[PDB]
Length: 139
Ligand SMILES: Cc1cccc(CNC(=O)N2CCC[C@H](C(N)=O)C2)c1
Ligand SMILES: [Zn+2]
Image 1 (cartoon, rainbow, N blue to C red):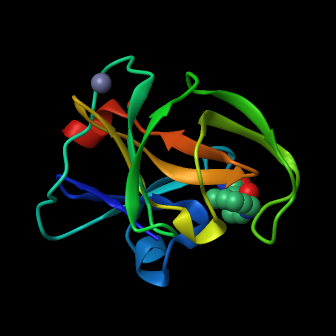
Image 2: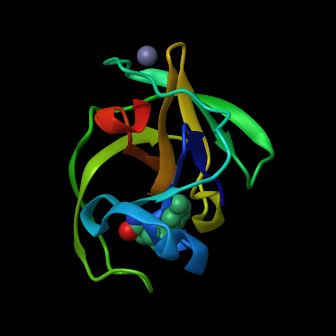
C-alpha cells in the first residue's frame, strides 16, 4: 500500500484504488497501473522532473529503504494476475531489489523528488510506475 499526495491529487496504484478514489476520479490508465483522484486537503509531496536512474525506495515487506539503479520508463511484458490480463505495462522502470505484492505503493525518490511507486516485482526484481512525465500534477 501507499500513495503520493501532491497539490489536490492523490496518486495510487490503479489496482489498489478505493471506492472513494473512483468517485473522485481525475485520470486513470490501466496500461500504466496508475489512478489519480482529487483531494480536499493540500498534499505533502513534490514530483521530480528529471532523468535520474538511481534513487531510494521504501519496501514495506522489510520496513526498510533500499538504494536502486533502474531502467528508463519503458513498455515491459507483465504476466496475468488477479487484477489484469497478460499485457505490456507502459512507463515501467525495473531494478534489482526485494519486493512482494503488498509492497505496491511504496515511493521511489531521487534527490529531486518523487519518481514513482512500486507496481511489479518478483525474483529479486522491483518495478516502478513512473510519474515524472505527468506535468499536470504540479498545477
Ligand atoms: C510487487 C510484486 C512483487 C512480487 C511479485 C509480484 C507479483 N504480482 C504482480 O506482478 N502483479 C499483481 C499486482 C498488479 C501488478 C501489475 N502492475 O500488473 C501485477 C508483484
Ligand atoms: Zn532526479
